[PDB]
Image (cartoon, rainbow, N blue to C red; front, side, top):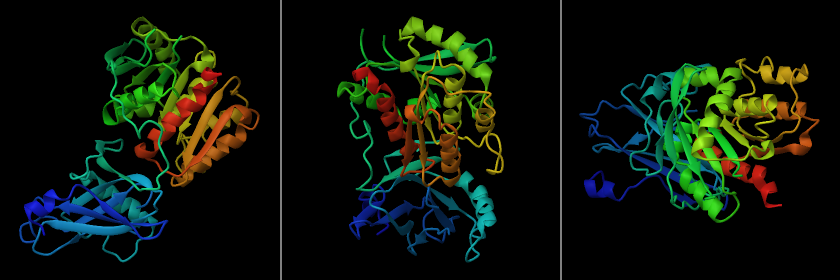
Length: 383
């Protein structure tokens, strides 16, 4: 116990079913600073997305082994991280009200890390690494169940925008070999380097639920740009349509039918995607919005989003749009903004794929609604 051979047998969280409908899960973490005599580390918080009154892990005394044991639904899937910290003044008061939590986690997350023993760990969105946890009854995810390595790899270029005054990476991936539908994916870096979307796109076209398509993944660059360009920015989409699509056409030709062009985003990208179809239905007729930030730009839920306001004012219309609209239950405020947007899209409820899902504000949940959405929106291609 604590020995190197004891650790070599450990490759991530272990679980065993307690009910038919509950699992017991245990996490391990090996302290790199040894036992309590030499180690700077007093607490190790486990921060589960969707789930997280807070508990640290527990040191078996005289070893480098920190351990923790919880319970998660047999159908539960989400990501987590560790936060080993030198300070145990945070989260010492027996039960915090909310303010203390926001504040507490605010100071800790900087130190967040993935689980070094868990293979399924990536560099994620909010500035720390996370790891992946899936439980046995977890709802199937199209294509992720079956990575089939791609035949030809995706093309990484550098789009130099004259309009935006920046450059960014773009990835061009073609499934199908000789009018391919186009799909623009925002947060491109992520679906390209964090959770390579390729082997998934290959498998699903291979087993013929995705048509041979062309995919363009656009770098968000950084948080400031993403915070300026994704949320309701006309210039971004004009640059895309004028400079990027044309540049892509030379590399990988796609159809110009709107009813088979897709824009797919999450959070700010979800907002962005809807904004793309609302304003340019002649170019983007397919909208896949997951966990879309329809509160923007108002923190609180006090005011409706700009985009919602703008529908209410009939300043914009959602004519000629098939849209997939997805939001989790474990993300309370986004769900309310999304069902509020749904209600305001009463007129075209016919051409909307409404999906209230199990999951959270989680790249591990989104990835399966991403694939399902593509399938839902391109199904008319198999008439």
